Image (tube, rainbow, N blue to C red):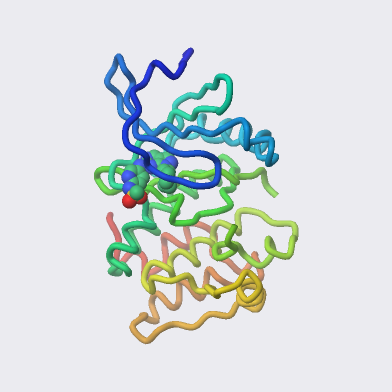
Length: 255
Ligand SMILES: CS(=O)(=O)Nc1ccc(Nc2ncc3cnn(C4CCCCCC4)c3n2)cn1
């Protein structure tokens, strides 16, 4: 591996905002298709995220579930780092949700199932993702769910997906990704996150006071799982397989 830019032709833009952009792109000589994140070194340490990115490449690259987006290599030049990324043909989950505004229960449970395994794997290797936002949940071609982003940690922007203990600031562990699974689960069937407000200030309270309600079209099966995960006291939360085990899941997923 010694990649310099001229080893690629760049396709259409893929997004995003925060750090620069992510591009469709193609390895000139094997004709390989990939996402090529381009991040200006300019706005990197000019923001202090740099060292908290190295040990997120670290984290990204030696990992390997099929339900986790893979990082191939990297490089840079004058400005900008370049992340050479697996490509997720069917786009993000954020956009599938806007498109269909809600998910059926067969589809949700599958997405949750896939998320557990990828998290359950992440948690054997003791790794904790922090933001499991739908912006970070891409889709493979078989429509497999693939986790993606960059705020991971050791053991032990919107708060919509964070749990109480974080937002205020306490000794946290892998019990965060399980609250995020709850927040997600809800968002999928309802289409909006259970703590949404129009301000960061409401949302903090809605989270602090665990303040959500279910629209009628939501089944006491799912109420039970989401109720269970989104408890305040971290130790209250199912462990990852007690989740997969959940009656409501199993009745509704792939395998
Ligand atoms: C616009 S869309 O409706 O969402 N279609 C779409 C979305 C994603 C992809 N593929 C893809 N593969 C790997 C990665 C790694 N990071 N990204 C980020 C791209 C920057 C925008 C934010 C999303 C994630 C990736 N995107 C293809 N098509």
